[PDB]
Image (cartoon, rainbow over all chains, first blue to last red; front, side, top):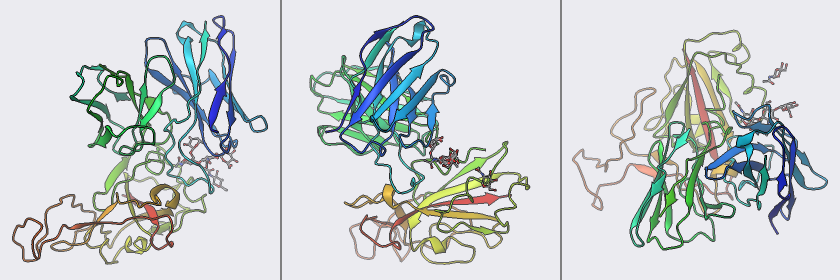
Amino acid sequence: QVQLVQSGAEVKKPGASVIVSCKASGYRFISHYIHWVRQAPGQGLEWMGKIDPSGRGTTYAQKLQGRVSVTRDTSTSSVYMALSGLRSDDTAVYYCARDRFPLSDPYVWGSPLGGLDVWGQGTTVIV
Amino acid sequence: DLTQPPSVSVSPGQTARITCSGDALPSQYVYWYQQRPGQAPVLVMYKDSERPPGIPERFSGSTSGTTATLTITGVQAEDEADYYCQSADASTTYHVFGGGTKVT
Amino acid sequence: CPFGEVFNATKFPSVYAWERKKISNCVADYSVLYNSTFFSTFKCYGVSATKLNDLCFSNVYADSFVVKGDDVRQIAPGQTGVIADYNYKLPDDFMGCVLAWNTRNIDATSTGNYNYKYRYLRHGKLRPFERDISNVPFSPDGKPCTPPALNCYWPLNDYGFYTTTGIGYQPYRVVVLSFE
Ligand SMILES: *[C@@H]1O[C@H](CO[C@@H]2O[C@@H](C)[C@@H](O)[C@@H](O)[C@@H]2O)[C@@H](O[C@@H]2O[C@H](CO)[C@@H](O[C@@H]3O[C@H](CO)[C@@H](O)[C@H](O)[C@@H]3O)[C@H](O)[C@H]2NC(C)=O)[C@H](O)[C@H]1NC(C)=O
Ligand SMILES: *[C@@H]1O[C@H](CO)[C@@H](O)[C@H](O)[C@H]1NC(C)=O
C-alpha cells in the first residue's frame, strides 16, 4: 500500500522555522527518491528539493539554497523538511511526493529522476 | 527554464494541444501533471510518450526538438484542470515546473 | 565544467542522429569519470586518462549516443561494421576518450525498447565525425523509391532492447569525448 502521509496544517511567524514530515509506507523506502514541491495560492507549482533516502545526498532549488534543509529517518520511514526564516511569499501548500523510478544496483548513472508519482496530501502553512 | 501558454480554451469535442518549450530539453524527459483544483497533482505522461495506468487513452505526449506537446483527443467536461510540464537543467538536478495551463 | 549535462542527461539520442555538446570556458575536473569502476570500456586514445587534469584544451566535444553491447567495439579508430561505417565514424587521428556503460536498468523495458535506431543501409561510407539524420527510402539501384516495393527498404532498423538478454544485446550508453 503506497502512500505518503504528511503532517497537519500550521501557522507561523515571518522567521519561525517550520518542520513538515512525510511518513512513508508500503513501498521499499530506500528505493525511490522523495521530492518536495510547494504551491503558492494562485500560482503554479514550485519545486524545492529532493532527498535520496539512503543518505547519498540532497539537492535544493537554486533560489532556496541556504534556507531549505531536508532529512531522512530510515527507522520511522519518514522524511522531514525544515524551512528557516519564512517570508510572506513562503505561504504555500507543501507537497511531499515520491519518484517513479526504482533505484537499485549501485546507481545506474544516467537515471530518470523526476516523475513525481504518489504525491502526499499537502501541508498548508501560513506565515 | 520551462515556459508554456497560460490558458487553452477548448469546447468539449476538439483537440487541445498544451505545448511546453524549454532550451535545456534536447536531452531531458518531460513529465506532465494534471491538477484539478483542490487536491494533489496526478501524473499524466512520463518519459515524453508513456502513460501510466489509470490515465485514460486520450492523452498522447510528444516531443519535437526543444518543445513538448500534450494532446487531449476528445476533450470531455472533466478535463478542466491545470497542466504542468517538468524537466531538469540537462543534468538531473534542479527540476523545474512549467507556468501552468488552465484548460477550459 | 558541466559533465552532468552530458553524462547525467536522461535522454541520449540514437546512434545515427548523434549530437555534440561543446564544453567551453570552464575548469574541468575529469576525475568524476575515472574514479568510477562501473564503466565497461573507458578507452582513451592519445591521452592516458590520468594526465587530463594538467592539460588545457581549446574545446571539448562530447558525442553521446546509445548502441548495443556488441556494437561498442565498433566505436574505435579504424574499426568497421554497420555502426562505424554508416552511423558514427571516428578518425584515424582521434585524440580523446570513449566511455561506455551498461544501461540495462534504464533502456531495456521487458516488453521491448524499440526507440533507438541505427542505419543498416547506405550509399557509401561516412566521413569521420559526420552525421546522416535523413530517413529516405533506400533503393540499391540508386533511383528514388516508395515502399512497399521490390528492392526498396527503409535504411533505419530498431535495436529492440530487452531486459532478459545477454550483455552483448543490452543497451550501452556511449559518450565520446573529443579534445582539441
Ligand atoms: C551523476 O549523478 C550521480 C548521482 O546523481 C546525483 O544525486 C545526488 C546525490 C546529487 O549529488 C545530484 O547532484 C546528482 O544528480 C553522481 O553521483 C554522485 O557523485 C557524488 C560525487 O562523488 C557522490 O558524493 C560523494 O560520495 C562519496 C561516496 O559515497 C562520499 O564518500 C562523499 O562524502 C560524497 O557524498 C554521490 O554519493 C554520488 N551519488 C550517487 C547516487 O552515486 C555523479 O557524480 C554525477 N556525475 C557527474 C559527472 O556529475
Ligand atoms: C578521485 O580519487 C582521487 C584519489 O586520489 C581523489 O584525489 C580525487 O579527489 C577523487 N575525485 C573526486 C571528484 O572525488
